[PDB]
Structure formats: C-alpha cells, structure tokens
Amino acid sequence: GSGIIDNATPTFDANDINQAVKVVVTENGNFAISNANETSTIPANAGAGAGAATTNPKNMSFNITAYSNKQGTVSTNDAFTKIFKAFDGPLVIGNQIKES
Amino acid sequence: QGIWVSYADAKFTTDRANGANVFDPNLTVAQQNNVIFWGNKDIAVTLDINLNGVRIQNDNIRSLDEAIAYINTFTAPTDTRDGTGVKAVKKADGSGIEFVNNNADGTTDNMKNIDLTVNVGNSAGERNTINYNANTGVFSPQGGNLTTAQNDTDWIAGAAQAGQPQNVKVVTAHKYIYSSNPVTIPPMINPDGGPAFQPNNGNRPTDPASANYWDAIQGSLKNTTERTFRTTEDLRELLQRDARYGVDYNGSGIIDNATPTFDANDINQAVKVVVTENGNFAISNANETSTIPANAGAGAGAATTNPKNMSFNITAYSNKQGTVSTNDAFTKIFKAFDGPLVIGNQIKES
Amino acid sequence: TKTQRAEDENDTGTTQFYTTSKNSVEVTEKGVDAGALFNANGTGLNLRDG
Image 1 (cartoon, each protein chain N blue to C red):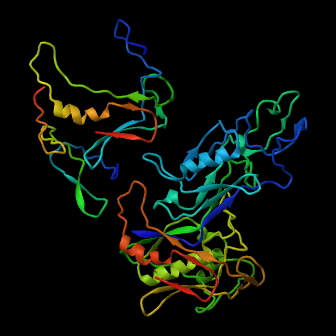
Image 2 (image 1 turned 30 degrees about the vertical axis):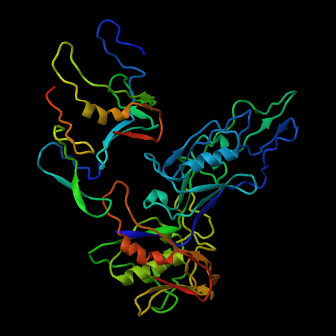
Image 3 (image 1 turned 180 degrees about the vertical axis):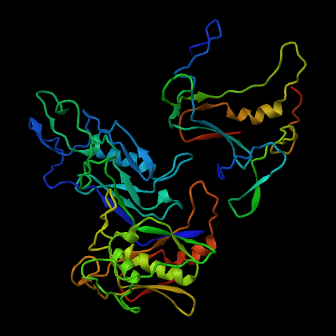
C-alpha cells in the first residue's frame, strides 16, 4: 500500500516481490496457481541490492471481471471471463492450489 | 527400471548420556544443573534440523510432543513440498525421540531409509542449566540464552567438530536396477561352495574373491549405491549379498564419516536365496549359526553369528524429476514377499 | 523441467512427448491459439479481436 508517488522513479522494494508464486497448466486442462511458503533469493547484482537478498512470500487475494474500453465498441466476452472467474476467492499461504 | 527392497524397518533413537537428568518442573531447586530440556511455557526451544533433505525449523516449541507433532507433519509429501516418510515417536523414557521408518511408502530416495543432520540451533538439543523462582514462576535460561547444537550431537552419541554438525545415517533398504548390457559382478567367498578364504596374515588384500569378502564384513555393502543386474542369477546372488551383509538390524547407524567396522551384528549368514524348478524364487532363514574364518575382518580369530529375524517389504523404483516409468507387473511378482519372516522352517516364495 | 533441454514452445513443430500416468505416450508443452478454446460443455468461447 505504498505507491508510485508523482514522478515515475522506480526502485527496489521490500516488498512488491513474491517470488515463490507459480502458474501451471495441469493435464486436466485446468490452470493452477500456487503460493509456496518457501522463501527465495535475489542474486547479485540484480537490482539492488549489491549483494544477495531473501524474500518472504506474501498473501494474495485474486479478483476478476471483464475488459471494456470507454466510449468503445468492444463487446464483453462472458464465457471466457467465467473460466477465469473461478479464481475470485482469497489465497492464503499454504498447500492449497486454486484452479480454473 | 528396478525395485526398492527393504529387509528390515529403518530405526534410530536419540541417545541420552547416562549422567543426564530429565527436566523436572515439579521440584523447586534454585537451579537445575545439566538437565535435558524440551521447552516450557516460559521458554521456547529452537530445533533446526534436516532429515531426508526436508528441513525442519521452528522456535515456538513448548514441549517435546509439539516437536513430535511438527516433525510428523513432514512425513508425507504435499501438493508442493516433499515428504520424508520417517515417523517420529515419543521415547518411552520421556527423554527424547524414537525415529522409525517403515520405508514401504513412496518410490524415491527421500522416502526410503533414515538420514538426519542435526543443524546448529537445537535448543531442543536439551542440554542447558536453567533456574527456578524467586517468587512467582519462573523458569529461566542461565544467562541468555540457551546453548545451541554446536558440533554436538546434542543427543547423538558422539562428537565431531570438523565441518557441519554431525549426522547419523542408517541403511536398511537397497535398490536394484536392470540394464540390457552385460554386467559382471564382483565375486566373493561363500561359506558353502567355491572354497575358500586364505587369511593373508593380518593384511586384507588376499585374492579378489576373498578381498571382496574381507571388505564385506565391514560396511562396504551397506552403501547406498545403486545395484545393477541383468541375468536372473545376478539378481538372486545380489539379493543374497545384501540380505546377509547389507542391513543395520541393530538400529546403530553409520554416524557422520564413512568409517566401516565389524559389527555384532549386521551379519546374518544363514540366509539363502534359491530358484525352485517351479520358477518361484525362494528365501530361507535357517536357525543354524555360522562361522567367520580368520583373518576375515575382524576378528583375528574365528567367530560365530546368531541368525536374526527379517521383515521384507517391497515397492517400486522411480527417480526424482525423472522419466523412468514404474513397471508394476514385475513389482508384483516380487510383491509377494511383503510379510514378516520369523526364524523357522517356513520358506517364502515369489 | 523433466528433460532439461531447452526446446522453446509455440513452434508449431518439434512436438514433444511423454509417457503418461498410465503408460500411453502423449503430447506435452504445446501452446494453442486460445481462439480455439472450448469449455467443458464444448461450446466455443469464441474469443475475438481486442
């Protein structure tokens, strides 16, 4: 809940990072998203910092709608937004894995 | 393709020193000495540890049983993290932990046998003076904080300052793998045909068939190395090898460095593996004792071994992150052996 | 991640196989136009344009 504040002057953060996240496609055809409790590392000299650094995974809360431009002619495509609409709940860190 | 084959269940136990005492919250002594300690409402204990490659870490421990539960949580693989298959149990003394593994689960290296580093930390390594009262409560560490694992083996029976903290390891289940190419096998002496074993006064090297027999009576076959085969006779001879010299029945363990020695016993010489004309394999465990000629090993003289009970159990091979496919039809014909084998005249068959 | 060779997807060629949970050999790692996708009912999602 930090924010860009006026000018676009990007910097390293603690954190926006949530490295352990994974997105997979199971043979069933369902998409899958997982949030491992495991920590990660950032090799030097990526960023910031000059040395190695480690990140704690953070909780996520997916929520999904549909695209539509202002004063535009694009039509909403509900059937697709549904197969993705499956993800709308909270995802606490843990062994559970949501699917489309 | 191949098959995991355990001859006996993996086992290990924490090892209290005889001079130690269990923590005693009931008594009011101003300061308990070198008592073992497993956390308290007042005091957390860390327990950094890594068994079978799955690191266990926590520092909110309040009692040993919480350690038991939290360890038990890792026994099975989850959606993500690997499971160890090892099952901790409270030690009867209330002193520590009894690790036990049925190694009948899973199909990879991590699920089989027991292995256990004891990482620096281990406030659950239970060796710290702590003190009671005055007044309300309050058990406290004697000068913050509690000591860590160090180069101990806080409970492991040994010490090893060199490098990483010392780890016991104990093999009971070997693996076997087929290959189309011809495969010769290192010959060794048998106490039946193919005689014999000339001692070479003191010094080991002798003839190669006897040389392998010399090393065998150390822990050389206790190694976790993979064992290849092709022709069936390879397989029976090799199963006989491992059955005789390849298991830690005592629940002792390799402990850190690989320094093999004679044991009483890993040996179970009377075991036999045969192929009946029906085509069935057969394994037998005679009540009869055997003898070890001088100067094999250790000892310098002759020695005799009592036969010991076995408990076969069998699964299927599969490498981590690999492409080998399980071959169930073969694992079945060997799956026939899964029950216990008490010493006696009964003979199991495939 | 199985075979760790780097063969990039979307080629519409170099299709690659794997033994399945049973034993049958089948296709893996192939991207699809997403304009061809159908739901469980077999109705077309009929995604288009922007």
